Amino acid sequence: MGRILFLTTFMSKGNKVVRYLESLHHEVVICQEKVHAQSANLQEIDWIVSYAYGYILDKEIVSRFRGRIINLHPSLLPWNKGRDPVFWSVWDETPKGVTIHLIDEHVDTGDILVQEEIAFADEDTLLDCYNKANQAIEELFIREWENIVHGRIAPYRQTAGGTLHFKADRDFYKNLNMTTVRELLALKRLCAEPKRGEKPIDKTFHQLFEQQVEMTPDHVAVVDRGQSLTYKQLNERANQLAHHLRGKGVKPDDQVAIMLDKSLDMIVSILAVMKAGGAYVPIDPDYPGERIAYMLADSSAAILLTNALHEEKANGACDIIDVHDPDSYSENTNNLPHVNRPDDLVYVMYTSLAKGVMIEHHNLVNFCEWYRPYFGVTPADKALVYSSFSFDGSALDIFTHLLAGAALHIVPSERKYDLDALNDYCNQEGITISYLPTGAAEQFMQMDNQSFRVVITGGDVLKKIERNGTYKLYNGYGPTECTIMVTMFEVDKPYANIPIGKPIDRTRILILDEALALQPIGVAGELFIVGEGLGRGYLNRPELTAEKFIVHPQTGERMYRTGDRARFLPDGNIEFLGRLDNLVKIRGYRIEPGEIEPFLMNHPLIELTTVLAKEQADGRKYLVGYYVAPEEIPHGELREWLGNDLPDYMIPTYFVHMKAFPLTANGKVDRRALPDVQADAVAPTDELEQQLAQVWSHVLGIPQMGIDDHFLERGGDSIKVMQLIHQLKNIGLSLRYDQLFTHPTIRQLKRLLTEQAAA
């Protein structure tokens, strides 16, 4: 009848389309590369049919063949023009369908021959969508082809609007497409960009404070022992001092060092530094003289607010303002003229090699403003200033409760470590809410308390949730870099791994793979913080800042690299599991012991596990799983147990039973005191996985296939997982595409295949 050029780079040469056309006695030339006018394929060609063709036709060709170039595009064509139409159809939540259409000079903007709505299920995977759509448009082709050849169809222009995507746009999401529609959209709801309508934070802290002074001026602000300052009193005093400070040349972004013990003077000083226009640098006087000299040196601070007591610890490093000298205090009690922007520094705190972290006003403001309503903080509340001067926990303590008009209580040294006496003080003063570091918290749970409405903990891994009090318990999480905590969770029931929860106002958290691409929900990956909490970075360490605070390759958003491992739960709450990915690997494999410990722990008989890597004295390391238990558990059983969730190379080669773990006084178990193991010290075991080793080797092109070896750390991909299953189905037993992403190693796949057809 007539000669047909079939243009495709993705679809096979055995398509239903091609075969139907041949069934009609058409000679079908198949071309998967870009052609020019001179090309031999273009000789004697009546109709050109393009299906998932990766190239653009030269305008010459499109004009000479005008009216006769048909394209099959799996989407409501106005929608999802360009690359990956089905994927973007699911992600952007556009209308669904398939369109057969004329080709014009632009990308899928030609007039529509025949169009048909399609529907996807919540439980279908993205691959399912892809295939169903291809199927539907092929069937559509077959139905309407005759009415296309006889030109008896009216092509109508496309509806205005629609969307266009390019080749690179799907990069960020390259891992998602074995994911389900439901799961994908959930990942969208969690991780996608913030909704329109928002505006930058326009306030500085001392603004919100002074406002809160005017609203509640007579109410107590901060209490130390018996003595108190009302919000008006505190504000006035801090204003006097601040007038003196700004009078000494303190400007926006200027560092001002404060070295004092927990007191009213400390609050006075912090607020004074703020009001005078600077950022404050907290120095604990109980630090070694060395770290003190260093904090003073690294800091550009020219002024030091301090006691006559701790004066000399400075060694004359800077100008000293004594908080006990009346001359340090101006007569003026009025608010100073505002010189500040929310992007000015509010404080610099050091972490420990010790880095000075620069936090801005809008960071703090975001945190306070999320804190007050979330915990329902009213002036009825009373809070503890517990955490050290130089930790961000102090920032939470002071600032979150000042702006809600609450009452700060200073903790004295004696009460601080005696949690029994501090409990007593809390019950006598009726302290409603506070933040205790993990382990301090756990201890307070022992003390019978009826003073707290809410306690908040984080900074170390919470494990004990049992408590004598009637109060709600919260586990939060967040680096000093992103201004205190970027997540919070309400602990309702016990957990083996207590989740860290959901993000706060104006902060998103992204679970990423090593390549900085999104992970599907439930799949572990590094935790990246995006949003309002991200600070300015480390002081005088611009390269280190450049390493930690990154500009996303695909996205271009400023994000923080925590170095923490974490994953999303189905209910959205974030779960913490380890750090970097280091300490040591094993046998050529990147391994985290932390990743293994929980899978070990849910074994009904063991209550505590830690796993370590030890040296064979050959220079490299092997894996030892340490477990506390009633009695020794047989190695085979543990190997199988871990084997159900983990890849074999993660399964430790050793498993020590102990009746009890040795403990350091501070922290839980000591590693140095822990026993050590030793050994002088793989191909497919059975012939089933040895026969699928062949199909792996043939899909991806590897010489040798191991039992532990992954499918995806070799560069397996959507196409190759498919090629795997498609090829295996007709030379062997079929598999499901989910099974391969859940059980991606060789022997895991084997465990399936063996327990699959046999049951």
Image (tube, helix red, strand yellow):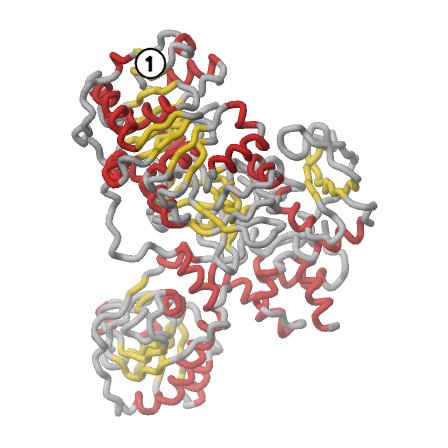
> For the residue labelled by badge 1, is the local secondary structure a helix, a strand or a loop?
loop
Residue 487 at x, y percent in the picture: 45, 46
* Spot occupied by residue 577 in the image (x, y as percentages of width and height): 57, 46
**Toward which corner of the image does residue 675 lie, by quadrant?**
top right
Task: Indicate the quadrant where residue 248 lies.
Answer: top left
Name the residue at 71% across, 73% down.
757
What residue sits right under mark 1 in the picture? 324
Residue 666 in view: yes
Vertical placement of 309 versus 381: above or below? above
Which residue corresponds to the image point at 58% horizontal and 54% vertical from the top-left? 493
Q: Nearer the viewer, residue 727 or 61?
A: 727
Q: Nearer the viewer, residue 9 or 686?
A: 686
- Residue positioned 76% across, 51% down in the render: 605
The crowd level at tag 1 (other Cα within 10 Å; few <14, some 14-19, many 20+) is: few
Say which amino acid is labelled 1: His
Query: If the image is split into quadrants, where does the C terminus sit?
Result: bottom right
Viewer-proximal residue among 474 and 754: 474
Q: Is residue 21 above or below residue 637?
A: below
Examine the rendering and report whether any part of residue 547 can be seen. Answer: no
Residue 280: image x %, image y %?
A: 33, 25
Q: Quadrant of the N terminus?
A: bottom left
Closer to the camera, 110 or 338? Answer: 338
Which residue is drawn at the image coordinates 68% and 40% (left, top)?
610
Q: Position of residue 17 (x, y in %)?
A: 42, 82
